[PDB]
Length: 152
Image (tube, rainbow, N blue to C red; front, side, top):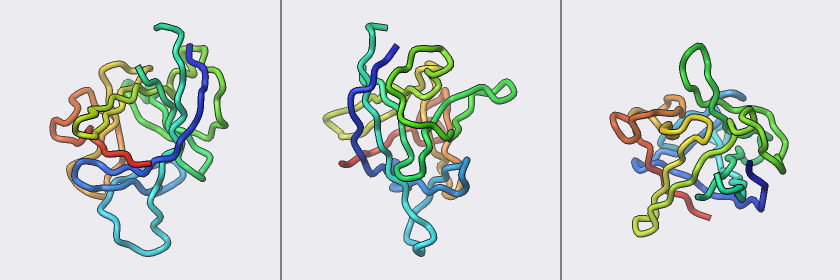
């Protein structure tokens, strides 16, 4: 279990300077943005949680679109999705742990990885190629990018 402490908004880019856009209500994509005002860069409203004991556990809100990121099984594959969810005070079930990621900062380099709490060993990643969905991988930074830079 995790209990909400506060939220803070951040810009995010991957290590190749791709940002996120909301391609459709259920899919984020990563691209090099310099487009029109129908392609609006996504910011994250990062909800920080305090654990029980069983670390910076966070939920990742898609700022202004009323969505949170989650990891769920689809078929037999771990999958990143976006779900309509309100702000969750208490994450106190295996089910709700789908919304929790461990924010893993490398302070010296200012980079960050996000590991799923529901699927340990799985990390948020982007394709090496632009205009592809944001996903999860158990081979972080291996023919994908799992390294991000956040700025508040």
